[PDB]
Amino acid sequence: STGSATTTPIDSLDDAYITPVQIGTPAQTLNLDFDTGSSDLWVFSSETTASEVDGQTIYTPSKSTTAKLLSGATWSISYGDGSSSSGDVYTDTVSVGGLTVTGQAVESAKKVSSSFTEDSTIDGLLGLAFSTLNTVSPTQQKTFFDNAKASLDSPVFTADLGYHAPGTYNFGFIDTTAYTGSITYTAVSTKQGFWEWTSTGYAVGSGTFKSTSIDGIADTGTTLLYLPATVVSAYWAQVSGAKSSSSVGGYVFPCSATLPSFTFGVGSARIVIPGDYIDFGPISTGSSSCFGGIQSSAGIGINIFGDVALKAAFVVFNGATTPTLGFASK
Ligand SMILES: CN[C@H]1CC[C@H](C(F)(F)F)CC1
């Protein structure tokens, strides 16, 4: 089997991407944030505290003839941005882009934090990291990809995120029309439950490439590119007036600037992030200070190749017995 679904930016900045997901019988379609940095499929639901729902589409398990309470199971998750959610668990039929999994754990939110209430565009998360991170207790549950894997034509999914435009998540096949040149594959460590890999280095604009190992995670559920402070300082030094602002919480730059590109290494290959991809717009409405798309990972404890990086590539998440990542230009 295969599946193919379009992913759409939630706003004009690409702060996140939503992908429609069918849950239950008859189908209830929710728009979920596909997140290669976590391993829970959770949804706004009929169980979510009413004051914490503001415009999201909810899953109602009582209206699904295939929904079953997973007796005794609870879940509770915290993300890197300090957001959180928790609740109980159903199994149900879940389809993405024509690919169907029966008996998928669908984590129903009883509580969500303020950032999830305040974002009407995201109806929940679909985790695509390794199932060792899944938070369901007392019986840990598998991701949608882990449940689908054996049925797929090839044990892979791909992320093809757009810049200010829709893109695609494919399951079970590699669309050879979706990228240029060749796909370079690189080793993955699953020891932290992430798609963790080591970039071979970077360049800033037309500058020389610096060969240096940068260990980090491929994380579709993080907006920005988080790298070591040395690398980030080197990038923003090329932008007149850019500075790290303690009050804003990262690098800002004059909105009048033209940003340089940023290149990262994948083995001997290179992925170029155009400068425009690094502009996250005014820090507040009408400001001439703009928020940078490359930020320091200092204090986070890991480097994160988030959407700013991934949207410059066609990315293969190879779930073979020994997982690997692939990157192509596009
Ligand atoms: C912006 N609201 C949420 C969206 C999901 C994010 C992640 F994917 F990481 F789970 C966290 C913040």
Image (cartoon, rainbow, N blue to C red):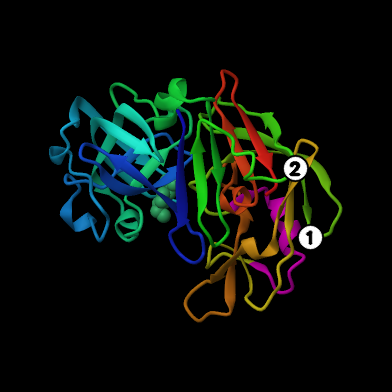
- The residue depicted at 39 percent of the width and 25 percent of the height is 147
Classify residue 51 as left or right of residue 171.
left
Q: At which x and y percent is residue 203?
A: 79, 52
Indicate yes or no whether the magenta region holds residue 311. Answer: no
Instruction: Looking at this view, name the residue that lies furthest to the right.
Output: 208
Of the numbered discs 1 and 2, the one sitting upstream in the chain is: 2
Report how far apart the C-alphas of labels 1 and 2 lie in the structure. 21 Å
Q: Residues within 10 Å of mark 1 (few under 14, many from 20)?
A: some
Q: Amino acid at mark 1?
A: Gly
Q: Residues within 10 Å of mark 2 (few under 14, many from 20)?
A: few
Q: At which x and y percent is residue 73?
A: 23, 27
Viewer-proximal residue among 210 and 20 = 20
- Answer whether labels 1 and 2 touch (C-beta < 8 Å): no
Viewer-proximal residue among 185 and 112 = 185
Name above or below for residue 63 compared with residue 67.
below
Residue of label 2 = 181
Residue 120 figure quarter: bottom left
Q: Which residues are magenta?
A: 225-243
Residue of label 1 = 205
